[PDB]
Image (cartoon, rainbow, N blue to C red):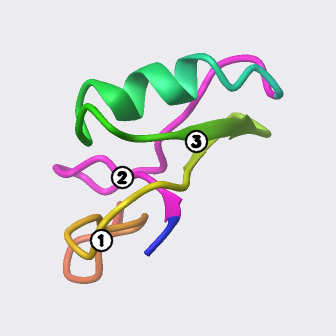
């Protein structure tokens, strides 16, 4: 159930730092979406790829960033 992790509030896209560097993506998903996660940095977006059914990926359905 993989994809870009999501801002659980406004459901704006979750922006990662310099693309390529799969360090911040990893870290971030580690310390919010669980100490067993993984991912990498696309074009200013953290695609995380180690996730469970109870990972949602951007946006939210019922409250995307309007």
Distance in Å between CA atoms under marks 2 and 1: 7 Å
Label 3's element?
strand
Say which residue label 2 marks: 6
Label 1's element?
loop
Q: Kindly indicate the quadrant of the structure image that contains residue 64.
A: bottom left
Say which residue label 1 marks: 60
Left or right: 34 as drawn, with respect to 37: left
Say which residue label 3 marks: 39
Residue at 40% x, 25% y: name it.
28
State how many labels appear: 3
Distance in Å between CA atoms under marks 3 and 1: 19 Å
Q: Position of residue 19 (x, y in %)?
A: 80, 27
Q: Is the magenta stretch mostly helix, strand or loop?
A: loop
Distance in Å between CA atoms under marks 2 and 3: 13 Å
In the rendered image, which quarter contains the N terminus? bottom left
Mark 2 vs mark 3: in front: 3
User: How many neighbours does mark 3 have within 10 angstroms: few (below 14), some (14-19), or many (20 or more)?
Assistant: many
In the rendered image, which quarter contains the C terminus? bottom left
Residue at 20% x, 69% y: name it.
54
Q: Does the magenta stretch include residue 18?
A: yes
Q: Position of residue 61 (x, y in %)?
A: 28, 82
What is the magenta range?
Answer: 3-19
Please tell me which residue lies in front, 63 or 40. Answer: 40
**Mark 2 near mark 1, Cβ–Cβ under 8 Å?**
yes
């Amino acid at each position: 159930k993989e994809g870009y992790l999501v801002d659980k509030n406004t459901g704006c896209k979750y922006e990662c730092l310099k693309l390529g560097d799969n360090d911040y993506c990893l870290r971030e998903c580690k310390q919010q979406y669980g100490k067993g996660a993984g991912g990498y940095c696309y074009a200013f977006a953290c695609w995380c790829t180690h996730l469970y059914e109870q990972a949602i990926v951007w946006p939210l359905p019922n409250k995307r960033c309007s």
